Length: 118
DNA sequence: GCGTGGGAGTGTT
DNA sequence: AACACTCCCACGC
Ligand SMILES: [Zn+2]
Ligand SMILES: [Zn+2]
Ligand SMILES: [Zn+2]
Ligand SMILES: [Zn+2]
Image (cartoon, rainbow, N blue to C red):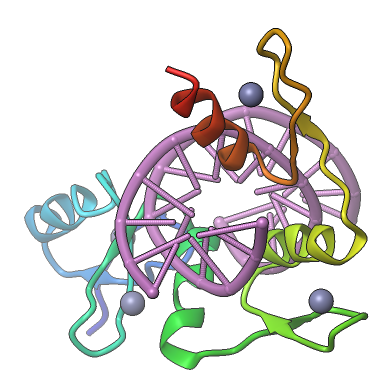
């Protein structure tokens, strides 16, 4: 005998003989943070799937993004982008305090500068 | 200054 | 939905 009922979630193929058991299962997808890491002793939950798959690069230590200049590898592409700013010397973020023409290569660098102005 | 995590907005298929 | 880019914010050295 096979079960009549099923979860309509795209990926949950759990089937139940009883409707009561499917009802309890249906509330598992009503997800505070559905995506959870299943690496040993991490169990960290995330809101999106791509955020979890980015986090799991910590357990594997993979660095798929490499700098074309200094050959250094990085775990994420955005961190590679600002690393290239270290080589090219560009500083888009400029301080907007009077009589202070100071530029930085990262937004959080300018924020730290704006706070030290006070 | 700069590596390197999480959150979130957006785009392409 | 999967996948990716890209930004801010934050922690750390
Ligand atoms: Zn389900
Ligand atoms: Zn994990
Ligand atoms: Zn480099
Ligand atoms: Zn300034």
